[PDB]
Image 1 (cartoon, rainbow over the protein chains, first blue to last red):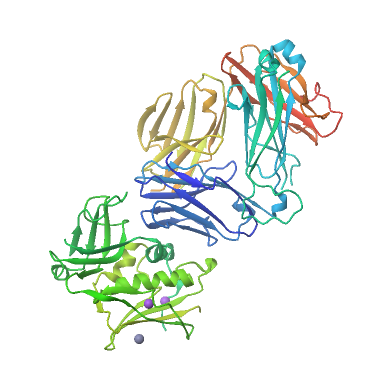
Image 2 (image 1 turned 30 degrees about the vertical axis):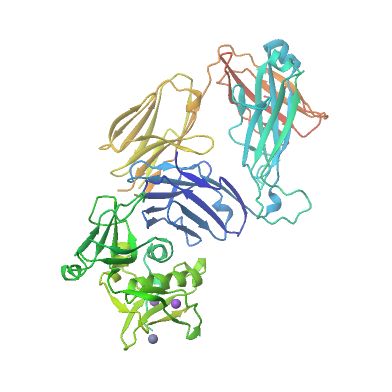
Length: 238
Length: 218
Length: 184
Ligand code: NA
Ligand code: NA
Ligand SMILES: [Zn+2]
C-alpha cells in the first residue's frame, strides 16, 4: 500500500521513551492507530480526521500521545514503557472512512535491560549422502541460534541471488529456554537437485538479517554491541 | 484567579488545542478579495482543501469586508466544516482585516509580561510580532500560545511535562481596555467549537500594546 | 460492540473450497475483510457492509439483517495461508475479531518418510536431524524432552519440477543425540 511506517523494528529498555511515525496516502483525510499483541487482532488506539483527533480508547492511556505534526504524517509516543507495550503498532488511512489501507507496522520489543539483546549465530548443514542416493535431491539446513528478540529475516542466496523456489522457513522462532527474556532459534531448508549441489562452482549462503540496537542506544557491556546486522554461513558444492 | 483547570478538560480537547496552537497550518495571505466569506481557490496543491470558508458571525460584520481588499491570519480546520465545495473546503473564524492603509513601516514586536505563580519571567521580544496597524486578537493569540506550548508545554498532558494547570492571556491596550481569554476555558473538544472564541472579528490597535500573561502550576 | 470469527483455526487441503464466518452484535455501516501475511501486512480483500462481492478466487457475502458476514475461498492455494480478519464499525471506532488462521496443506503425490543426519560445513562435530517427504496429515512431535528442539512442519515447493516437500528439523545441545528415534 501507499501507507509508510518508521521504524519497522524497535528495541527499548523498560522505562524509556519511544516514537513511531506514520506516512499515510496524501489524499486520505482519516488516520488510525492500532495495537496488535501476538496471536490477537488489532485493537483500536485512536483516530484523526483532518487536523482533529476524534476518539481515544482506554488502551491509549496518559503514557501515550498521538499527534499530526503537519501535514503529510502522524506520530505516536509512548513514555515510561512497560513490557506489556511490546506489540505490533499498525497505522491505517481512509478517504471516508470507507476502506482502511494499512501500513507495514512498527514491531516494538520492550526489554528489562539491553544486555538481554543478542545477535544470532548462523550455521549451514551439508546435505545427507543417503538423501542424494535415494530422492535424487539435496536439502541444505540453516540454523540461526541464540538471538533476542525474535526480530529476524532469513533468506537463501545461491551464487549471489536470493532464491524462493525450494525454500522452507519456520513460521515463528522457538524459545531455547522456555518460561524465561529467553533467546530464540530459527531453522530453514533449501532443497535443490543432487546434480546442482554436486557442482563445486555453486555457492550456497544462508543469510539472517537481525534487527537490534541503534547508534543512539547506550552500550556498557564488554561484548560487541548487538546492532542491526547480517550474520551468514556459507557452503560450497561437493 | 477563578480560571478553568486543565484536569477539567474534555476527552480530546487538550490534544486538539495542541494541534490548533502548535501543529496546524494557519491561513496567512495579504491583499485578497471575496454571515460567511468564501475564498474559492484559496489553497493550491493542498491534498485536502481547495476553498477557505471564513465565518464572521452576522451579515453586518460580513458587509464590512465583502468585495474589498482583505488580509487573512487565522487557524483553519477541515473537520465539521460546513459550506463551500463538499470535502474540499477548510473553515476559519474571523482573522479578517482590511488591507488598505493597515501596513506598518517597521514590524511591531508585541512585548510580553509573563508571570508563573506570581513570579515575573522574561520572554524574547520576537515571539509575538505583526506588520498591521489594527490586528485581530487571533493573530497575536495564535503566536503567544505557540511560544507557551513550545517553552512550557501548555497543551501537553501532566505525564508529558505540562506543569501549567491555569492560565490567562490579557491583550492590554493603551487606554486601559482589556481582551481576556482563559487558556483552559475550552468550548467543546473539536476546532469547530474551540475556535468559536474568534467568531467576533475583534480588531485592536498594535500601537503601545502589550500582552499580560498569568500562568499557574497549581 | 462485539465481533467473533468462526472457526478459530482451519486445516485445509490444497485445491479445496473453504468458508470463514464473522458474527457481529449490532447494526453495521462499514464492514471490512483483511488478510495478514507472515510479515504483518494487512491486505484489503473486501469492503462489504451488505450484499455480495467477488474478487477472482475470493468472494464475500454480508447478511446485515442477521448480523453476519462470510468469506469464501475457492481452490485454496498454499499462498492463501495466514490470518484472516473481520473488522466492524461501531455505529468510526473499529473492532477486529479473534481471527481465523488458515493452514493450507500441500498436495503430496507419493509420501516417502525418511529421517536424515546432516553435518555442519564449518569445522565442527555439530549435527542436525531432518524428517522429509512425509504426508501433510502427519502432526509434528512437541517438546518431548528439554535441551532437544523439534521445529514445526513447513511446506516447500520447487519450480522446475512440480514437487511439494514436507520437512521438520531436530537438534540437541547433548553431543551424542541420534536422528532415527528423534521424530517419535
Ligand atoms: Na513579543
Ligand atoms: Na485557566
Ligand atoms: Zn497590561
